[PDB]
Amino acid sequence: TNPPPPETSNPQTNQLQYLLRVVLKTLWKHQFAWPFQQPVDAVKLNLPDYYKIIKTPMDMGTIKKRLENNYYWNAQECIQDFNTMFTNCYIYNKPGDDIVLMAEALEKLFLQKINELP
Ligand SMILES: COc1ccc(OC)c(/C=C/C(=O)c2cc(OC)c(OC)cc2CCNC(C)=O)c1
Ligand SMILES: [Cl-]
Image 1 (cartoon, rainbow, N blue to C red):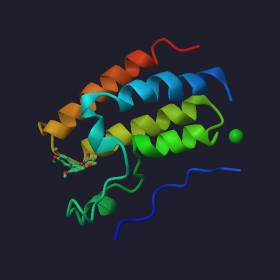
Image 2 (cartoon, rainbow, N blue to C red; image 1 turned 120 degrees about the vertical axis):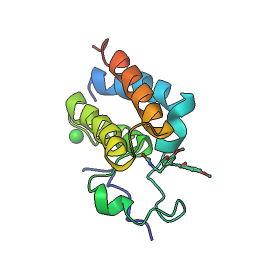
Image 3 (cartoon, rainbow, N blue to C red; image 1 turned 180 degrees about the vertical axis):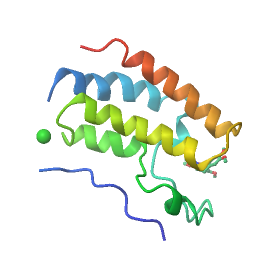
Image 4 (cartoon, rainbow, N blue to C red; image 1 turned 120 degrees about the horizontal axis):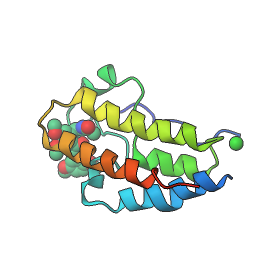
């Protein structure tokens, strides 16, 4: 069985609104977005070692749930989750894999969207 997804509720800056409404939304509609739209389903994908290697898992779906529930206090905490998501992919998969190239293309576009923020 897969581990439970990361918590998405803690209990509104302009940069957080921008990350959700502009950065995340554009990356969510990118063609290479599908493997990162929800937590890695290690059971269905038959990856019994994923959650042994990746100890801080993260996906765009959990970012959205966190951005919609005001989980983050600031934009830096949210930007770290994206970097957690990208670096997780680089750690588990092998260089040259198509998913690694997809993650690189997503990150390089992510740095452009955050390169112009309030
Ligand atoms: C029906 O097939 C489906 C349907 C829905 C899916 O997700 C919604 C997926 C997810 C596939 C992957 O995630 C995936 C894809 C790879 O190449 C394409 C890969 O190459 C080594 C390693 C992984 C393992 C995860 N590695 C990560 C996340 O970095 C597959
Ligand atoms: Cl808060």
